[PDB]
Structure formats: structure tokens, C-alpha cells
Amino acid sequence: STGSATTTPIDSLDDAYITPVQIGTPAQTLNLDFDTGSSDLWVFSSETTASEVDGQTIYTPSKSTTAKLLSGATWSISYGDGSSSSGDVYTDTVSVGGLTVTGQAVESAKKVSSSFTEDSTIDGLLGLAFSTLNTVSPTQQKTFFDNAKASLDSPVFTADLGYHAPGTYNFGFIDTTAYTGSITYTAVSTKQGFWEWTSTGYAVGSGTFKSTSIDGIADTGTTLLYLPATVVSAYWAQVSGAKSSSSVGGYVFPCSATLPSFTFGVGSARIVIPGDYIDFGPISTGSSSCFGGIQSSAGIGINIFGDVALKAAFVVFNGATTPTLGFASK
Image (cartoon, rainbow, N blue to C red; front, side, top):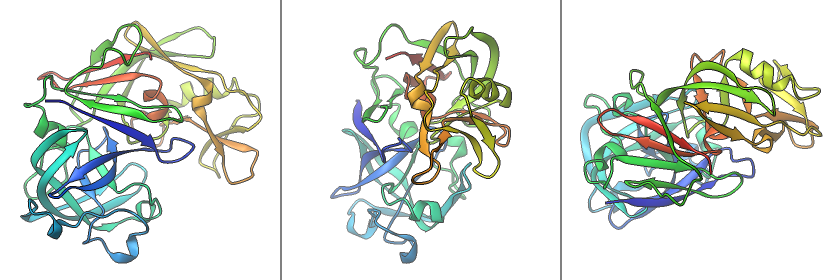
């Protein structure tokens, strides 16, 4: 089997991408944030505290003839940005782009943190990291991909995120018309539960490529590119007037600037992020200070190849017995 679904930016900045997901019988379609940095499929629901729902579409398990409460199971998650959610668990039928999994754990939120309530466009998350990170207790549950992978034509999914435009998540096949050149594959460590890999270095604009190992994670659920402070300083030094602002929370730059590109290495291959992809717009409405799309990871503990980087590539998440990642230009 295969599946193919369009993923759409939630706003004009590509802050996140939403993909429609069918849950239950009859289907209830919710728009979920596919997140290769986490491993829970959780949704706003009829059980979510009413004051914490503000415009999201909810899953109502009592209206699904295939829903079954997973007795005794609870979940609770905290994300790298400080947000969180928790609740109970059903199993139900879940379909993405024509690919159907029966008995998928659907984690129904009883509580969500304010950042989720305040984003009416995201009805939940669909985790695509390794199932070892799934938070369901006392019996950990499998991700949608893990449940589907034996049925897929090939045990892969691909992320083809758009810049200011829709893109595609495919399951079970590699669309050879969706990228240019060849896909360069690179090793993955699953020791932390992430799609963790080592970039071979970087360049700023038309500058020389610096060969240096940068360990980080491919994370569709993180908006920006978080890299070591040395690399980030080298980038922003090429933008007149850019500076790190402690009060704003990162590098800002004059909105009048033209940003240079940023290149990252995948083996001997090179992925070029155009400068425009690094512009996240005014820090507040009407400001002439703009927020940068490349930021320091120093306060995180891990480098994160988020959407800024991934949207410049066609990305293969190869879930073979020994997983690997593939990157192509497009």
C-alpha cells in the first residue's frame, strides 16, 4: 500500500504545516501537524477542557463506531518549545492520504497548553519519530508509520514541504518526479528516538564550504533551523545590522535586508536554503525588526534541522531495519 497527502502552511510565514487525517467511522477529518520529532498522535477532542478549545476541530470518539477506549491508558507530553498536552487513549481507524491503519492509538486530549488553544489551525499532532518516544502509559503505543510500515510497498515516508506553498507527505514510495538530481542517503542514530544524523558542514551565501560535523535531528514539527552558536554567528555576520536580542529571544535583522542563502552538507551533497526562507517577518506587527529563521541551539541541547532546512529539500525517512535519511534538491 501507499498514501499521499497534501500538507499546507498554517499561515503566511510557514510557521507549521497541517495535513488532513481521517479518524474513525464515519471519518472525522482533523488537520494535524506531522512531527518527525515526536511520537504521539494526539487530538483535540470532545474530552478537551472546553475553555481550552478555541476553533479547533475535535475528535468525538462516541460518534465513531470503530473507537475503543484503551483501558487504563494515559498520555502526557511536553515539547521543546514549552508546550504540553495530556489525556486518555482510544484505538480507532486512521487514514492519511488513502493509507489506512486499523487499531491506531489516538490520544485524546483532556488538557492542552495555551499555545495549542491559541492556534485554531492545528487540531493535534501526528508523531513520526521512533515509537520509543511515545508517552502512553502503562503500555507504550506505536506511531502511525510503525503500524503501517509492514503493509507499505517500501518502509519509507517522504516530506516535501513547500516554501509559502503546499507540499506533500508520501508513505510507502519515493516520487522520483518530486526532486532533481539524486537522493543522498546518510546514517541515522535512533539512540535518542529521533531521526538524528550528522551534516558534513555549511556555507553562508557564496562563501566557502566549512567541513565540520553537525549532529542534529530532522524535525518537521520545528519551524526554524537551530545550529551551534558559532555557525549561527557566522551566518548573521553577513547581514548588516543583524544582532542577537535577548529581549526578543534570538537573532533579529532589519526588515530592509536581503538575506544570504545558507548551505548544509549531506555527505558530499549540498542543500541550499535560499535567503528568503530565513525571513520570519516583523517581530511584532508594524516593526522594522524581523525575526531570523536560523537561531542558536545553545540553549536546547541538540541541533534541529526544522522546516527552514527541510523545505529546501525532498527528504526521505527510510524506516528499514537500519533507518537512514535521504536528501535531494528540488
